[PDB]
Length: 226
Length: 236
DNA sequence: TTCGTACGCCGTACGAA
DNA sequence: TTCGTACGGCGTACGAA
Image 1 (cartoon, each protein chain N blue to C red):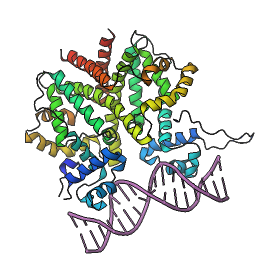
Image 2: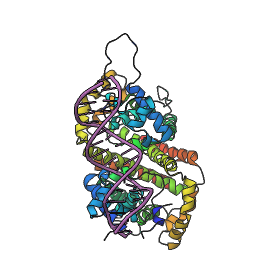
Image 3: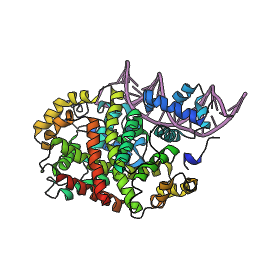
Image 4: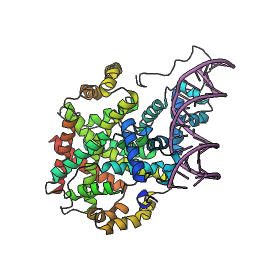
């Protein structure tokens, strides 16, 4: 079924994945097509298929590969708050570095490659110490993973949009001002209007915001532990 | 520009029969193909074929496919069955909103793929839906930026949970291999991973990952319940 | 193992009915 | 307003060296 059960038989899987990552970073996941990645290696297009069954598969391999960039200690430590914060910050760093992770990862089956499993051991590890049911642990970590991914999924959404359309967030908001006005005036959308200033140009910036929400989230996990 | 600033062309002035092809009609057909055979099928040719129209005839009403999908997104959000005012029971209000969104997403799995997550969708249906959600916590005396944070935490939980639920669904469509089946075929490899000894936590959590104790509905609710509890704490 | 050729998809530019 | 034709992409099946 999966690619971690389907091992490969210069040109190698490891070399194709690392090239696909390089194209994806440099020119966006849409550029990392079989021909372009093969061109990058000097290979024939279909030569890649000897090492990688399908493109869906190549992307899963791409996903695990980049996760391996994570700089994480072996043991999480006793400061679960600090541990989860670090894991969170490294993931955000990663995603910003590889914006295509939000698009590429189709979200069905979990990725059980080595790098993902290492990363997940660390996260699941932080709360393993405490006396909680398996299903409570998964819930609490789901809430954690949720906050981080969602926040970062938006951050990276704008980034990728900016690449494709050469129109960044300040610029998009600027050009929507007129229509926003119409919406505000319509009177049919009070809340939208109350919240527009902060939506267009936020008081505090992404780093500050990511931290606050994380801080709150961890606080609630703490409450759940008691 | 965006699409909510780019209306379909005015028809020529005439007392005689209208002529079928319109933006509203193209969107509704794209949604139907997307639901029936998955977003990948709802291509310009397939949607035109559905209407009996020529492929490029659609482009008179819709600038780009990226645009058609935004229109698709707002269209389906309009299916939300929601009261006008949210009510005083913010917990009840948010629960309902959450359940309806999940219901929606399960009904239109392509929402996870379609919605690219950059700029917000400022179509009518999205704005109505957002008014209701933002509304629930408007009553309380909180800074704009606190309100957005608290609602972001909410939207986070719901989307992430549902994004996985729907991930499996779509995968099952494409590969004809559902979740039970995938887990079943991964058993061997999970064994190897468990035995390796290099992944204790993975092993501790495998039974529940393969075949969960409680099911999606029960699980979605628990997490939501917890999430709301923390928002409650934040209000105090 | 390597890879050239080919098929059937896609979004959409162009220009005439 | 409609849309046929065409261009340059895509993933990948097939079959030959």
